[PDB]
Image (spheres, coloured by chain):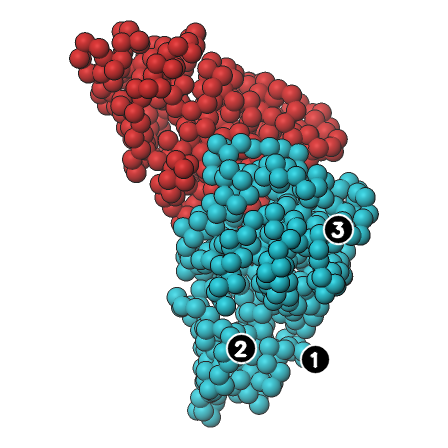
Chain colours: A red, B cyan
Amino acid sequence: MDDYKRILITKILKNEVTEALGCTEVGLIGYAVSLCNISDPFSIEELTLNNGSFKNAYAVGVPNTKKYGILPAVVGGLLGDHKNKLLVFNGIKYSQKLEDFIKERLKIRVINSPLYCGVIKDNSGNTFESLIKDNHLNVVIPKINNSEINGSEKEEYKNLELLDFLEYIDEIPEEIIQLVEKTIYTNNNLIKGDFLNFGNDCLSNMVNKTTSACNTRMIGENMPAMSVAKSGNMGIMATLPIIAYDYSNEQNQEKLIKSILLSVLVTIYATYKSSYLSSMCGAVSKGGMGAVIGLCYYKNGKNIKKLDSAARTFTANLPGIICDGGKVGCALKLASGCFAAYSSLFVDISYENGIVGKNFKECVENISEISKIMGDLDSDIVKIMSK
Amino acid sequence: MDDYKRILITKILKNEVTEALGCTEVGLIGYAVSLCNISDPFSIEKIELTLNNGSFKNAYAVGVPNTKKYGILPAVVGGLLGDHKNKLLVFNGIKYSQKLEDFIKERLKIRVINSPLYCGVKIKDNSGNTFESLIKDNHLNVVIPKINNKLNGSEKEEYKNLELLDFLEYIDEIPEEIIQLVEKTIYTNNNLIKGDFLNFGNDCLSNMVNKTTSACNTRMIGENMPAMSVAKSGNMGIMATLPIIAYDYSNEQNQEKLIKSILLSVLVTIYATYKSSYLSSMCGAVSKGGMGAVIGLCYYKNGKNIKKLDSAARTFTANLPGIICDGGKVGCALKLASGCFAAYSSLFVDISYENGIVGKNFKECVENISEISKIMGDLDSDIVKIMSK
Ligand code: SF4
Ligand code: SF4
């Protein structure tokens, strides 16, 4: 209908929906290490990360290494090129000898701060330092210019309503339809085998597929994930429950496309609302709100009261949860999210009950404010993991 | 097993496992209001209820018995229509009058404070008379007027130094009094099941979530039915017992096995509560009762297996940590439902200790969970600040 709304939503969809090869933090570490440009990787005789980064990278698989941790990311950066940027681990040939070489020399130190990735000395004596700072991945020392969006457009998207999202998925551009199809493609390709299949009912398949794709993204497979806001697990949480619900129901193409589009709209909105960093698991919360709105739209159509009830039951169900770092166990958390979505399709919770919001907007507002309240917990998380 | 261990375990089980009629916060509010002993409630000009963060949180959206209503204002009306001599049972035998609710709604000015349990009522009437009442610290102690009511640590600390092996050996030589306690617990909690709350199938976990949420919803809406509570947290007891009851209902139908598993669940729940010595806005009921329930479920499925119980604890710790305690509500049941999930998912998945906050065994898992609860702190003030809108 409206013009400014369609163009803003289309632009933000083209912006937020990207492809991230696995965990972004190991990718950033490898990119910084390749920016150090060590000529002979075996000639090395210095990594500084913030609490959240060290947490997320302590037990996550690095692409094309079949290993977990920060040392594989550093070795892959050594064996990578700066021109690949966040895809620094592409085309590499992992050498166990270089891993064993760097293990004795890689001295890592953690700091309490926002995003900070600062790196090495060689046999000759030369020292090469590099730094990547701020929430937006901005290189400060290699100065290699290279996603952002100005605040006015984000603010205009925050001023949208659920009705606007319902109207947008009825007048979808062809580029956005193909984007949704490519998203479903990338995230469905992440399903490899069984990870948590405990039945043949709908929620069984939902949990199975979601946990399998999350585990695939975690174990360091060389398969990209269609991420929203550079959080791949958030995109998995937003898309896969809806995919598996559609698989166990009508097997509808356009219906699933529209439901996932509304899910992504809700996810982008929630991420915009949760403007502050948080140690609360933002991926689970936001992706699950998106997924439950999409599932309610698939079940009841364009029904405002049903979507409000789903958001209320979700807010009452699984609010507040720790983001203890990218891990194989993260899949389990997403599994819980699936539950929180399905349970919200059959339960009504009054607005008075606790932190529950009065509608979709107020639910998202309350969840975002509580995420702001839970605050900086990454310091204590890193202190715990070190033991 | 050792003798001192068995005697301590029996004492602590008979101590923590009590019967709570629930809805204790609205009951406290109604009792404080009834201590004013208002003969004619309709002569009031302004009421001033003062609650602490925790009390206002837990009583904001809980059902009041014999009122069929939710909130603090129904509790205030029920206290006005009650007698102080009824103590916490001010709401028994009452006939709720919508007219008195509509009258008091215009005059009830509630104010929140940052303190331990505090319920102070200050009522004025048309004549000019003022009636004050106050309840401080524990529940049972009214200060205005001065009807005092007083509420060892060595036993708690000795219980903290036990191992899961002690709990496994105790459920093999159980005294008869403790067996009767477990059976009465199962009876009380199965009687709390009233209808369906989240039944979307006839499979095992469907029954688990359904029955658990049904009994929690029954305890929440203000029914005058007692609940077998552990550490006076009824939802904790439901979370610890009912998942095991429902898994046994959908599997082997074994009596002594279910008794032993629920006893181990209660042991693990009490242990987790003892370890989390500091207050937290994190949902302690879900966490502790679910740790008990998942240990009991692992004991029912795989028996006396240390690695199996370790894996269950690891997957549980990785699964659903840090849920909010946003006040006693109908939605609380949903959280408990999630707990069921968090337990069942741990019976078929192993999570390495390297994955995040997970500990190397059960003991370390509980220790990390307790430390994170201690770190999260109060936060209830901001919770009520959010709820007030
Ligand atoms: S818990 Fe959620 S936010 Fe934290 S690492 Fe896992 S997927 Fe990401
Ligand atoms: S939300 Fe959890 S901690 Fe809070 S009252 Fe309900 S069961 Fe207890």
Q: CA distance from mark 2 to mark 1?
A: 21 Å
Q: CA distance from mark 2 to mark 3?
A: 35 Å
Q: Disc 1 on helix, strand or loop?
A: loop
Q: Is residue A39 visible?
A: yes
Where is residue B199? Give x, y as percent.
Answer: 74, 46
Q: Nearer the viewer, mark 1 or mark 3?
A: 3
Q: Nearer the viewer, mark 2 or mark 3?
A: 3
Mark with earlier residue (1, 3): 1
Residue type for callout 2: Leu
Residue type for callout 1: Gly
- State the residue in front, A57 or B145: A57
Mark with earlier residue (2, 3): 2
Same chain assignment for discs 2 and 3: yes
Identity of the residue furthest to the left in this view: A125
Q: Residues within 10 Å of mark 2 (few under 14, many from 20)?
A: some
Where is residue B362? Give x, y as percent.
Answer: 55, 43
Q: Is residue B47 visible?
A: no
Mark with earlier residue (2, 1): 1
Q: CA distance from mark 1 to mark 3?
A: 37 Å
> Within the image, what quadrant is residue A205 found in?
top right
Identity of the residue furthest to the right in this view: B253
* Pointer 1 residue: B93
Q: Disc 2 on helix, strand or loop?
A: loop
| Position of A118 relative to B192 (above/below) | above
* Pointer 3 residue: B258
Same chain assignment for discs 1 and 3: yes
Are circles 2 and 3 on residues that touch, CB within 8 Å?
A: no
For residue B140, the mark is: 2
